[PDB]
Length: 103
Ligand SMILES: CC[C@H](NC(=O)[C@H](C)NC)C(=O)N1C[C@@H](O)C[C@H]1Cc1c(-c2[nH]c3cc(F)ccc3c2C[C@@H]2C[C@H](O)CN2C(=O)[C@@H](CC)NC(=O)[C@H](C)NC)[nH]c2cc(F)ccc12
Ligand SMILES: [Zn+2]
Image (cartoon, rainbow, N blue to C red; front, side, top):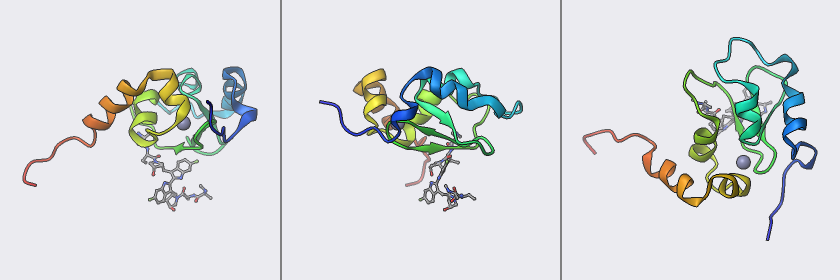
């Protein structure tokens, strides 16, 4: 069974892509990578949200993988779990935050 979707209007990849009209060229993550991972542009800075879980992410850095960030921050997202599988999410959740030594 499928649970709630926060934003039905953005459930399609094409709809999410259309939001990235004014995506800043300086950001080292591309609209297609974001849209594929469920994200659409909110229209300010580099803020995006997931159509399913309504999780917002910003301050995208060089080397960021939207699927990994999705799983790092919103592991309970149903779209994420169905697209990537629970094992992907669990792996990401076991990996981050990186271990710091001392206790
Ligand atoms: C940087 C780490 C993280 N980014 C990354 O890891 C990137 C990929 N890779 C390195 C990130 O973006 N996060 C981590 C989570 O925390 C959620 C998100 C930050 C965020 C919060 C987000 N997540 C939180 C977690 C908390 F425990 C406390 C507050 C927050 C917030 C709100 C932040 C903190 C403070 O409230 C001000 N604030 C704002 O968004 C202010 C900015 C003017 N503006 C507003 O409120 C407007 C009007 N409404 C939202 N709200 C958002 C809304 C968005 F559309 C986009 C991102 C956010
Ligand atoms: Zn999500």
